[PDB]
């Protein structure tokens, strides 16, 4: 059997630790034997980024924008500990933050659902996608302890100068000031609109604009503006926009059948991506995809580098690390590249490999992370390589 | 059945007030020799007194230690027109809350044939909300064009922080919170947890907010340190967490803890977690103070839409369960404070009578969508209290 021809390149970003180990196996067992595919390769392993003073990350980001579809392996974000461990020059910045900013993108988290690994919320029959506005607010704020009897003002200073009284302290406390940006919020809404049209799902956005009548209102107003500018496009895709109050939204989410994109401001999105992921089960089944306003797509698994399985691997051991999310990053990228190039055999292949993973799990062949979520409970689990071998087997059955 | 000391009783509004009277005269008073220190916080009585009976009610509670409050109307423009008021008076709940320096705790009532939407949740999750400050007392502004925005602290120490240099347009916000308020919050949480014998989970994003969220983290720990002996005695563990970790863990847990939340978080999570349990009709609510005062209330409102039907001569299926458990909560707390273990035993029996009513298939309408297996029919308000009465008589 001939390999399926992929017309245009996919940009591939290699990563770190156990993620990197899985990545190599997926390519060799599940991807390269079946596809004649051009991969524009950037090694984003910590030592390559260290060697090039992180310039390789920017080059990677440029390539993703250029070709339009990327697929990325998880990477170490160094803290002081990693600097010591890998003898780094510097605590380089998160490759993800660098790439996301370069691409003006928003990250969308969506669970893979499998019949025999049901979510922890009974109602949830369809994936809930979390899209987080990852700019500003608390994450770029400035703060101060206020001990004394004091007055605190926010000063706006140039065309129209103004002073606002934050608080007249009599006793002690703390103060915080934050900002966000029109352009940032517009890009976020635009990326949500793109993702929802692509996925054919409704958009829920929510704030507490009844309290925050300028700041939260701003996001509400911008989001609605962007939806209005895309009224027909949204309606053609069957996408409904639902603006809610944030506490109402959270209550309704938990109550729903799932199936929507929940667009969240920065802090809420940080919390809810984790909380909703938890409601679905294992992080091993969480996919992630960056989408930008200009239609650039970058697929990744939602989890990290899985360093503690990696430390076990370094001692010679097989692990039971779940490759499922990494596989679906590959198949997501492949499908997208296929849809763009107009090459339906490419989409078909991505469908078949995805189907092979799901068939593997539903047939009772799981890695260790899925075990406490199985129904009926599954007693046995296999190593990462056994799992990939079973996926390969089930792929062959469909080809 | 005696009850050594009085309880402060706060009458309310609309359908809530209607259930209130019904419950006293059918389920409480026929069984207990109590001095209720009565305050009518009905909107008409509040308007006449210029909101003073509200303040009067709160000063009585602080004195007598235990209060029980009916849902009241918080007036807006529509309500001013409806009841022909003087002003849109301030929320009684918010008025009392501040005076008593209390924090509110929400706890679902669990019932076997009305299961939560979250499978793992086997024990109630209490949400305690720090209902002062942050975005609720924030100051905000739209920013156009090139501009520099700054945070300026003035007086004992003088400080200017660049918030942002704007090239395009955007928005800014500044907020505050207070040492005292956060301490009172932590104190109330510790009181509640010791009373309920549950663990305390507190969480922030102090890995990002290294001064502001850290302040809450440090103060909460300080207050736990101050009371570690009694906490250890009651079997209460304190578990500080990162906020996003906590939320993931809560959904993953079997319930059973108090989750203390900062203002915004608590606004969201109270509703979210209530939703995970089922019907708002099975939600109890208690204000605890740092000094140990308690005020028991239903979580629900006045149910105006049921009240209007009532005035039109229709029968409703309004749920009194939350109301009754506000009464029993008050009765039990007052029983244990004097040392009268018969008052407590009645509080138990009435709660257990309600639970037996529901579990036998006798429900109000609001429960129907949640019951498992589903109940084909529902009973009215009057009929539900009558069955609760039957089932209480069976236990006495
Ligand atoms: Na998070
Ligand atoms: Na709320």
Image (cartoon, coloured by chain):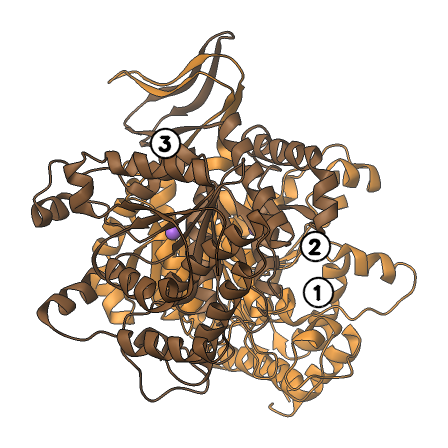
Chain colours: A orange, B brown
Residues marked 1 and 3 touching at CB (< 8 Å)? no
Q: Residue at x 69, y 70 (%)?
A: A323
Q: Are marks 1 and 3 on the same chain?
A: no
Identify residue for label 1: A23
Establish if B325 lies above or below A43.
below
| Residue marked by disc 2 | A15
The answer to whether residue A59 of the structure is visible from this angle is: no
Q: Residues within 10 Å of mark 1 (few under 14, many from 20)?
A: many
Q: Is residue B131 above or below residue B340?
A: above
Q: Secondary structure at mark 1?
A: helix
For residue B95, side relative to residue B176 (left or right): left
> Chain ID for label 2?
A
Secondary-structure class at tag 2:
loop
State the separation of the CA atoms marked 2 and 3: 45 Å
Q: CA distance from mark 1 to mark 3?
A: 49 Å
Whichever of labels 2 and 1 marks the residue nearer the N terminus, that label is 2
Q: Quadrant of residue B63?
A: top left
Disc 3 secondary structure class: helix
- Relative horizontal placement of residue B217, taking residue A132 as reference (left or right): right
Circle 2 Cα neighbour tier, 10 Å, few/some/many (<14 / 14–19 / ≥20): many
């Amino acid at each position: 059997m001939e390999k399926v021809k992929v017309k245009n390149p996919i940009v591939e970003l290699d990563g770190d630790e156990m993620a990197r180990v899985m990545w190599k196996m997926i390519k060799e067992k599940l991807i390269l034997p079946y596809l004649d595919i051009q991969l524009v390769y950037f090694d984003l392993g910590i030592k390559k980024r260290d060697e090039t003073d992180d310039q390789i990350t920017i080059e990677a980001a440029k390539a993703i924008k250029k070709y339009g579809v990327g697929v990325k392996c998880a990477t170490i974000t160094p803290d002081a500990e990693r600097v010591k461990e890998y003898n780094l020059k510097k605590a380089w910045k998160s490759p993800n933050a660098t790439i996301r900013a370069y691409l003006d993108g928003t990250v969308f988290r969506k669970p893979i659902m499998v019949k025999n690994v049901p979510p922890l919320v009974k109602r949830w029959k369809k994936p809930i996608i979390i899209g987080r506005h990852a700019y500003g607010d608390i994450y770029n704020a400035v703060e101060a302890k206020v001990e004394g009897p004091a007055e605190v003002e926010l000063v706006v200073r140039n065309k129209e100068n103004k002073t606002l009284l934050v608080h007249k302290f009599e006793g002690n406390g703390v103060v915080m000031a934050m900002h966000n940006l029109e352009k940032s919020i517009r890009s976020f809404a635009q990326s949500c609109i793109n993702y929802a049209i692509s996925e054919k799902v409704d958009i829920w956005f929510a704030t507490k604009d009844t309290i925050s009548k300028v700041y939260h209102a701003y996001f509400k107003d911008i989001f609605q503006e962007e939806v209005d500018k895309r009224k027909e496009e949204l309606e053609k895709a069957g996408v409904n926009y639902r603006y809610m109050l944030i506490d109402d939204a959270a209550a309704q989410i938990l109550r729903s059948e799932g199936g929507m994109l929940w667009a969240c401001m920065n802090y809420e999105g940080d919390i809810m991506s984790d909380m909703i992921a938890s409601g679905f089960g294992s992080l091993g089944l969480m996919t992630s995809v960056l989408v930008s306003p200009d239609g650039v797509y970058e697929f990744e698994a939602a989890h990290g580098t899985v360093r503690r399985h990696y430390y076990r691997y370094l001692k010679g051991e097989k692990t039971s690390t779940n490759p499922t999310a990494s596989i679906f990053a590959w198949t997501g990228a492949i499908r997208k590249r296929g849809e763009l190039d107009g090459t339906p055999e490419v989409c078909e292949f991505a469908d078949k490999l995805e189907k092979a993973v799901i068939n593997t799990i539903e047939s009772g062949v799981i890695t260790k992370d899925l075990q406490p979520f199985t129904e009926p409970p599954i007693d046995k689990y296999v190593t990462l390589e056994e799992f990939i071998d079973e996926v390969k087997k089930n792929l062959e059955k469909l080809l």
